[PDB]
Length: 52
RNA sequence: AACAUAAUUAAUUUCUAGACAUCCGUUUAUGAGAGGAGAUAAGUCGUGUAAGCAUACUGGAAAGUGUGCUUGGAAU
Ligand SMILES: [Mg+2]
Image 1: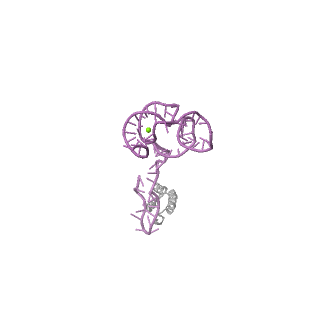
Image 2: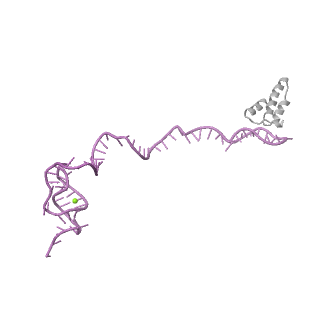
Image 3: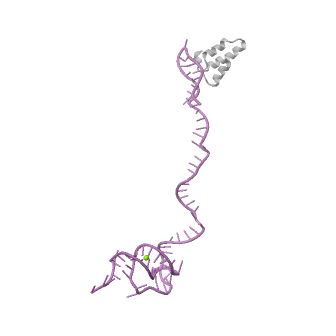
């Protein structure tokens, strides 16, 4: 899932709310939270920030 | 070459990139060389076979001669 979101931001393409939702849902470790925090930041600064 | 992302406010991206690199041809002029027509004006030796037109030959090249035509000659 990380790869999909990274490609979208590289191409300046919108990311789905379901995509970020799946990431937070599948957090399995303390380290995973740190990565999810970065992607929540990226989602906020994206075209579909309102749809969180 | 022109897709796709997204979508419980709605928007984003796309909305291309190659290829003119340059002609064939075209006009103006520099102009070796060779004439033509003028300007300045004294030379040159010539100059009565009616004249002219067209044409041919011969004239160091005004002319002469042939052939037809014309009177813009003469002719009781
Ligand atoms: Mg003659």
